[PDB]
Amino acid sequence: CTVQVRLELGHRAQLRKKPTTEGFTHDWMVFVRGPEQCDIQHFVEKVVFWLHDSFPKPRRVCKEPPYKVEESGYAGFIMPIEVHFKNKEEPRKVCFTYDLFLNLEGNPPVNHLNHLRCEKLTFNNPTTEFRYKLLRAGGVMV
Ligand SMILES: Cc1ccc(C(=O)Nc2ccc3nc(CN4CCCCC4)[nH]c3c2)cc1I
Image 1 (tube, rainbow, N blue to C red):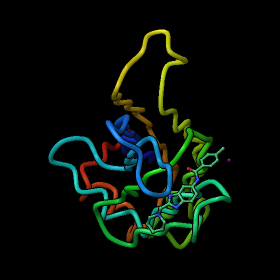
Image 2: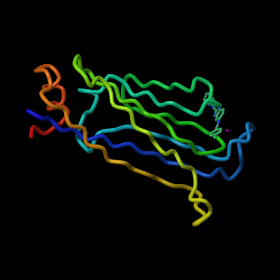
Image 3: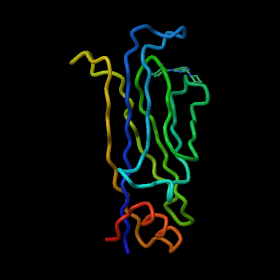
Image 4: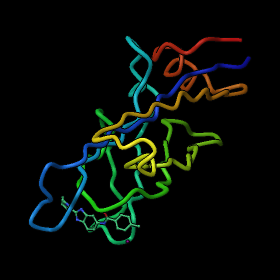
């Protein structure tokens, strides 16, 4: 059989009225979460957010929900996001290339923004133990 589950990747960003002592101009948050009333913790081991090299501890890990990183900084960047599964067979993780953008190139000028990216994952022939976790999370058998 085939089991599909859904992830939502997203972020929010806020232009600061005044920059931090550090000069940070934006506050931002990036997340991985399930659709409403779906508990992805059943099948997600951890979520690794790979921040820009300039960040201290750029490898940010959440082993439990919420799977998110709140930060402040100077600029947007491309953020690899690994979602590791509670799975003993391949694949044990999926990697997303997440566009963490902090403005719209002043066209138009915004002082905040939100983005959501809905992702479907398809697991062929999961083990009994991993099927239970996927379906327990609200996954659909196909
Ligand atoms: C292309 C590019 C993109 C982002 C940054 C950036 O925001 N870097 C940055 C560098 C150091 C930072 N430190 C923080 C603050 N956190 C607070 C929580 C504890 C660790 C430090 N945010 C930081 C943000 C720099 C470049 I060049």
